Amino acid sequence: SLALSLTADQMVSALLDAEPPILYSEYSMMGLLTNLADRELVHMINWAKRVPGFVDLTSHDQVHLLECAWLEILMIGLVWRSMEHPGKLLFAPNLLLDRNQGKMVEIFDMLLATSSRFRMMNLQGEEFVCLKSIILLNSGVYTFSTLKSLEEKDHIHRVLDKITDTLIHLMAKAGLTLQQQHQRLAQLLLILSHIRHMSNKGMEHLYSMNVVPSYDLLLEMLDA
Amino acid sequence: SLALSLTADQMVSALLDAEPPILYSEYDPTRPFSEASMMGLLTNLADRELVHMINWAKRVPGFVDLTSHDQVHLLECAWLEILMIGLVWRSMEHPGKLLFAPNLLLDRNQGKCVEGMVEIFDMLLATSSRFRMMNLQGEEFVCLKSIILLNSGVYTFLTLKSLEEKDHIHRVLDKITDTLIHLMAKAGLTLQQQHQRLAQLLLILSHIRHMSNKGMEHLYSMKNVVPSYDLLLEMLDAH
Ligand SMILES: COc1ccc2c(c1)CCCN2S(=O)(=O)[C@@H]1C[C@@H]2O[C@H]1C(c1ccc(O)cc1)=C2c1ccc(O)cc1
């Protein structure tokens, strides 16, 4: 597998060069966020096709992973943009909202606590792209009966190992001791639990409040 | 604060001794089940397990350093995930089956007489397949279940006292990471393997969190089953 022969720095370079652009709101917030997320989705697809190992998977498996990950990925992008703005969520450069204005207030607070935790930890951009790759490959991997699917799962897990190794390398380069490398790895992956939880809450708050991209839509966008 | 002084070997031992008992389900169930009666057995088992889960939590190194309010907050956020990982562990040796209790072993086809539950089944069965394929060790299971207790609710805290406890929580989590790695090293794993397995284990926790969210919808919708703040409170003060 082409993904599996990459070094850490080559993996990090691939992800960095695949990063989607920071988009702008075009001006009711729900409409502004819906429009913004819809335009963000088109870039997420094309970024995902550039995650090493992702296009080795079958188209069906690619859609399943994107189905499961799409909101976690939008959310981690949001908390990364809002990192250097304590107390505010940087939805877009022209749409920077705070708690009162933001609210739906429960979701808002959890996002602010995620951003603050990333500020606390001095999360680096090279680490962020790795984390967002892990979300793409991990979130749907436990919910795919055949020998093809067994291979696909095995492939995903070996690419996930390659990203783990990449993360460890980045920390070792920054001088962290081995004890500090394992600890910080754990800290990063434990926040991914919180993101899933925020994604699930956002989903159910969407229901109580169509806008979720369908399996067929994702497959159309992936295949075109 | 004795908690952060422990070595890895004494962390394992502390958690192993803290493991709660395996309870039996209600012995006289009419079968086949209906939706109602199955829920009745499961709710009843979960309500009895919850009592023992409190006693275990108070023996997790560092848990009782927290204020009582924050102990409850952590149990509120984690209680279903902990019931689930325990269920997943019990069922490792039973492919295609969930061992709720030694006398309540259920297949996938039984889960569907509860309306929405078969999907959760499907997900809990796959976690037990995963754990079996990684040959998840008991000592690793007790570390993971402790991480859930302290992690699931930490991101929703906090002011100085709050920042102190969140830092105390993360320093215990760091100490359970150190422990997991120590286990992997003595089992002989290369460092590369030690890190890859740690990651593998911690990413499964995100799935467990999904399943809990899934399940919790159901309990609230489609609520009195969920243990209240007062109920947890007070089980905690019964010291
Ligand atoms: C085959 O019928 C099912 C199966 C799953 C579900 C339902 C029916 C109803 C809809 C919700 N789900 S569920 O996912 O939320 C939850 C996880 C597990 O099953 C449920 C359950 C439980 C049931 C009643 C409660 O009062 C408390 C918890 C579970 C449990 C109980 C004890 C354990 O020691 C470990 C896990």
Image: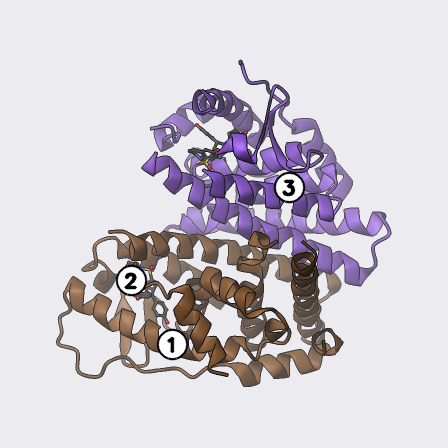
Chain colours: A purple, B brown
Per the rendering, the mark at residue B164 is none
- In the rendered image, which residue does mark 3 sit on? A115
Q: Is residue B133 visible?
A: no
User: Which quarter of the figure has residue B36?
Assistant: bottom left
Q: Are marks 2 and 1 on the same chain?
A: yes
The image quadrant where one finds the N terminus of chain A is top right
C-alpha distance separating marks 2 and 3: 34 Å
A139 or B162: nearer the viewer? B162
Q: Secondary structure at mark 1?
A: helix
Up/down of B133 relative to B51, above or below = above
Where is residue A193 drawn, in percent x and y? 54, 52
- In the rendered image, which residue does mark 1 sit on? B49
Up/down of B118 relative to A215, above or below = below
The image quadrant where one finds the C terminus of chain A is top left
- In the rendered image, which residue does mark 2 sit on? B224
Residue type highlighted by circle 3: Ser
Residue type highlighted by circle 2: Asn
A70 or B149: nearer the viewer? B149
